[PDB]
Image (cartoon, coloured by chain):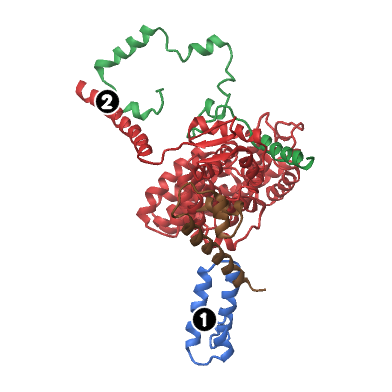
Amino acid sequence: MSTDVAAAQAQSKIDLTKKKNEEINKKSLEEDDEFEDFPIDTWANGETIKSNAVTQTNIWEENWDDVEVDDDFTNELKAELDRYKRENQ
Amino acid sequence: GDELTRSHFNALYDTLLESNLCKIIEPFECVEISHISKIIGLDTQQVEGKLSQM
Amino acid sequence: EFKKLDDKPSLVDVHLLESKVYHKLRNLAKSKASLTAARTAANSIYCPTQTVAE
Amino acid sequence: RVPNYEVSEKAFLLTQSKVSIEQRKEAAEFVLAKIKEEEMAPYYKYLCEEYLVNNGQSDLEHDEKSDSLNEWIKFDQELYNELCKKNESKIKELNEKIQKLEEDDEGELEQAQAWINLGEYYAQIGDKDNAEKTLGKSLSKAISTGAKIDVMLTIARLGFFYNDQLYVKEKLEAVNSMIEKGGDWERRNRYKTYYGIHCLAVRNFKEAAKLLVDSLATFTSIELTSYESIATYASVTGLFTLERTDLKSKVIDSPELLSLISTTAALQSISSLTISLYASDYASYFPYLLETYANVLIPCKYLNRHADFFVREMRRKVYAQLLESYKTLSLKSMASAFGVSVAFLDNDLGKFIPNKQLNCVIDRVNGIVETNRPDNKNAQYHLLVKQGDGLLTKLQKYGAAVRLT
């Protein structure tokens, strides 16, 4: 579990005996692991992580969607509605 | 009745328009489209559409 | 099939038809390729005036 | 082998229920005829897994939802029995033939080839796990490098068949390694077509364009969805990636696209749009955009991920080109050119402008649209610093890491 692309930070530091325990010490300092407490707290598996296709699981390159609206519905109405105003003028 | 004369009369029309349009507006900058449409011998909207593509 | 039965000056015609079909399908790549074939085949001397005209 | 790709495509219409009513009906009957005849029964069961309370469901061998607009996917218990009959009988007979060949001598040729025949039967009926293992035996035995490529490709087809992209990804990496080692051009053509469609299913259509233009020039049809769909794929990527001039020369550098003419609804709808962008028709353009959504994106397996993504992007392009060519426009006229009303037009534009991939502003008092895109020394300066910042960052972390150790 790493932030953004994992391999970019995996190469930055690998396993060393000096730092290994020190890694725990920082985590313990903040107090929790903070990825296992949120499910207990909410008291059910979220649906706000299934809020978009990418939010649950991303095996894609980010679209930049986070609003996800079908735009074919509104455009179809735009074309026809404009046409009527002109026809009834 | 002949596909070839229509084809190469459409091409000739476009390249003829192109040579003329450049030659008009060469000693210019911020030239009104009304002037251009007169000299080339076409319409104001027609002039705008060709400019866009070029 | 008439390349197993090749003795034919009548495939010269078939090449020229082939060129026209491709031209109207608006590919000139293989209209040129067949037309080139037809020129080669008529270089050999048996061809009517009509055939050379086509 | 060849039958798989037709079945999946029709099956994707049953997966959807946002498609046309008569279209989905037709597709169910075709799939049912070939469930009887070619054993497509394991993959029919695979369709309900892809639901569980989702539309397009009606199964009665599994979970039902006749609330779904699809009610032509319904199983029969004749179907459940036909499955089990053929499945067992065929595996048993075909295997016994193979066992005999193993007894007899020569394994270089005879036995590896015999194992290919098992993996083609499982490929056909949609068993991925069972195909992989037996074609796993063919590869183990030393053979031609061209054959090894052919086999990996048969396996790669199966990932699109279930429409699992991860399975393809993995497998096409082994093809790339062995494509040079064989050095065969026969299957070099196939590989680009496969890998083209993987790029199509993910968001990088730029790569897809580069592989699929090669696939026009030479197409390899076995195990690969038919040539009218391949035209439709080249045209999709063409609209997204290129701009007027480039687009025009691409489809005149492909004679085959024009000579194939529209011979299917999806091909028609994409091709209508191709012309209008490069001919700089805006008038009929705005309707064609709607047609492509309906008849290409949702019916297609790989562009159904791109249904919202495509429409959003394609509108930027058509506006972009017009605004670059103009210092100023009037809004009412710009609205008329496309065929929308004035107020309607802003809304689409107003999502594109702050992302700043359209570089413009809109006066609502003059009613003029201002274009204040640098295209001079200032633009090159603006781009460069982002890369040079990137270089600073790369060095900041790597520098620290080596010094501490």
Label 1: element kind: helix
Image quadrant holding the N terminus of chain C, namely: bottom right
Chain with green colouring: A
Determine the residue positioned at 45% across, 41% down. D170
Amino acid tagged 1: Ala
Label 2: element kind: helix
Does D388 sit left or right of D54 as displayed? left
Q: Residues within 10 Å of mark 1 (few under 14, many from 20)?
A: many
- The blue-tinted chain is C
User: Viewer-proximal residue, D215 or C27?
Assistant: C27
Residue D111 in percent (x, y) is at: 46, 55
What residue is rendered at 64% in x and 53% in y?
Answer: D268
Q: Which residue is drawn at 32% across and 14% down?
A: A23
- B1 above or below D352? below
**Residue C38 got which mark?**
1
Residue D231 in view of the camera: no
The chain letter for the residue carrying disc 2 is: D
Relative depth, front residue between D386 and D302: D386
The image's mark for residue D396 is 2
The colour of chain D is red
Q: Which amino acid does label 2 sit on?
A: Gln
User: For this view, does D57 lie left or right of residue D345?
Assistant: right
Q: Colour of chain B?
A: brown
